[PDB]
Amino acid sequence: TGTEIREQLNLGGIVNAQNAQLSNCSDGAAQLESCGTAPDLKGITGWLNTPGNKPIDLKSLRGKVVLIDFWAYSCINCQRAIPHVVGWYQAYKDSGLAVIGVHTPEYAFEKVPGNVAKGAANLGISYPIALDNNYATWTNYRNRYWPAEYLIDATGTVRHIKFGEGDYNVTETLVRQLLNDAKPGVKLPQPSSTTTPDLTPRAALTPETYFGVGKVVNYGGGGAYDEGSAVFDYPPSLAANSFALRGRWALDYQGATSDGNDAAIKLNYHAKDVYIVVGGTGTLTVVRDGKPATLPISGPPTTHQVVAGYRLASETLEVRPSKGLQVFSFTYG
Amino acid sequence: TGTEIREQLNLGGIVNAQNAQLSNCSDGAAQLESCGTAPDLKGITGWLNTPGNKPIDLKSLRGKVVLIDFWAYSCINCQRAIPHVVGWYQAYKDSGLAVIGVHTPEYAFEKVPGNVAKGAANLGISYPIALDNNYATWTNYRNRYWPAEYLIDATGTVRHIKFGEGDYNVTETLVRQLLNDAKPGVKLPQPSSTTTPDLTPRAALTPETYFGVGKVVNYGGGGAYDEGSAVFDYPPSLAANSFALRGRWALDYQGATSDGNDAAIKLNYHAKDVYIVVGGTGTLTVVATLPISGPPTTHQVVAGYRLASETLEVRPSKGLQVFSFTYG
């Protein structure tokens, strides 16, 4: 619980000497604001896309505009947003913009450097990536969500903080301004938003559907939802925007593992697109509106799309994962 | 942590069969949305401003447009919001608007119907008040913030959900539409916003400053801040948007009770106005004297010319229980 002025930053964690002024910025403001020296990138466990994979200290980037992009490679929101950041990096890197993709993992499998690499590569990320496997940077920045952005001017001052997915032109407008502030008279190409479509969904999709025992919020099958292995069935009626389980499942704090050959997930969802975050090796059989699809699942746990709909609508879904597949979440678009 | 699309609802609690569709609305949309039958007002512990303080059942308000307004009387955001709500109610109660002020206490003292009644009166609230002392309605509605608003149409369907303070015209515009859908051709006065100013601060004030042990986030004093009594002193340097203690204090989950005669609080804030939420009887001295008595509530300790980074100190007499600093 809390109180809130609309458009206010709802900052995570606690204030320290480094990040005490962040709250002087509001959330995704259209004009530059001033909210303190950027906090250190603390406790980064590893770096990609830098020479020798050596760290970057923010102070080495004074004189440059710095964009801090919090992301996780299996987050569908981040996947939708990152082509914009890529866009910006490619348009402005030679004009004074530096970008650091702070990868703070949502799931334990996102801690694996190799998996982050493959993710960044799928997304065409060539800017420095800081692996924040211990949330040290996330905490120090008082972040609360994926995606999130902190825009730092040539002075090392945070001027713009944006939580959540969307409003790219607002941020890019400010990026262009700060690049001029750093180098007055700088000539910039047309905005990257010219050739990068905004594919942000209407913000009324089914909320992120966690299967983890400590994050689940829309398990609608009744009975307990505790960690360990048990047998489940679908309830007489499943609520909207909710899931139920059938067959035997092993639950834990990462997600729900298929522990039998009859295992199934029923999902009522409100979205255009639906993704499952699943790991392991095996087969996903998905049934929607009497139409079945079969997806081979293997390698790095990530998002696999299971519905490519025509519009935002309420629908029902069934997914049948072969034994040993581990389901982390449903996410939406 | 969690993932977010901008302007999505950040609903609290969990999904039950009564509120499952709430996430089908976004946060404060300018167009009418459709996100399910309004959930029951459940576990309401008492009622004010109804006949005989009897309960109101939402199903008996079908045919009317119904604004559910979550508030707490010591919440300064809510105090700024309520005159807009009061304004809507005065303007539209005879055109089909019902207004239910669900009072969910932010603190233990806000559980006292007396204290609530007193707060409502200072805010000129004449509409029904549902006392949500066990957070059952807050929960059933999956709310997360004071203030919050859920707008229900005459068929019982939530059509608008708005978290946080501001954008009054957006909501009122939808209220007017829903009144027309409930009673086509209905004639309405000019928007209440015409004569009720929007005094919403820039959304970059110092974050609400809790003193309760469980909710503190900006104690910049260093050292322990746990339950019990102890002696304190101002740290060598105080971080911005933070507070520091001095003298003796008893620290519970509700707040920081002033013990010794020499107790003081230093605060670096970023705001135009600063208010303290303090209980107990005695004297509050700010660096000016302000006598503190009766229902624990907000007291204004700073009324500034403009939004400023500044510092203040308050010296509360023994006994005074400080719950928070809030801002404007």
Image: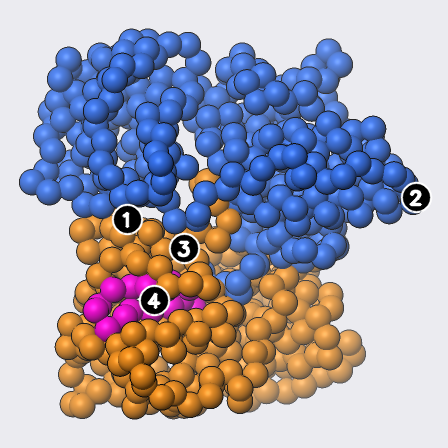
Chain colours: A orange, B blue
Q: Do labels 2 and 4 share a chain?
A: no
Mark 2 packing: few (<14 Cα in 10 Å), some, or many (20+)?
few
Q: Is mark 1 on a helix, strand or loop?
A: loop
Evaluate if marks 1 and 3 touch, with contact meaning CB atoms under 8 Å apart.
no
Is residue A139 positioned above or below B127 on the image?
below
Nearer the viewer's eye, disc 1 or disc 3? 3
Which amino acid, by three-letter code, is at mark 1? Ile
The residue to which callout 3 is attached is A26
Which amino acid, by three-letter code, is at mark 2? Gly
> Would residue A102 appear left or right of A208 to someone viewing this image?
left
Q: Quadrant of residue B50?
A: top right
Which mark, residue A150?
A: 4
The location of residue A228, given as percent across then percent down, is 45, 58
The residue to which callout 2 is attached is B185
C-alpha span from label 1 to label 3: 17 Å
Magenta: main secondary structure equals: strand
Which mark, residue A14?
A: 1
The location of residue B300, given as percent across then percent down, is 37, 25
The location of residue A55, given as percent across then percent down, is 17, 79
- Looking at the image, which is closer to me, B293 or B59? B293
